Image: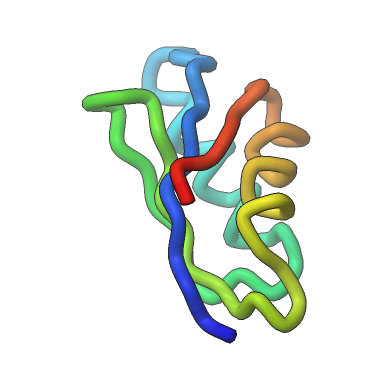
Amino acid sequence: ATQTVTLAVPGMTCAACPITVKKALSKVEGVSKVDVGFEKREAVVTFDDTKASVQKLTKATADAGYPSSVKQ
């Protein structure tokens, strides 16, 4: 498939959480795109559910350095 979810990365590293998380989901695996929003420490990513999914998105920012979650 090809869907996009939002993620919760409360790392607030000051202009760093949204940089490391963005590249995390963008490189998670099947991701097709990614983004971030310091307005609520969350990262939004688009991808192909055939090779990835929310689980892998939160896992990408999670391996980036932030215990995050997802908003489906």
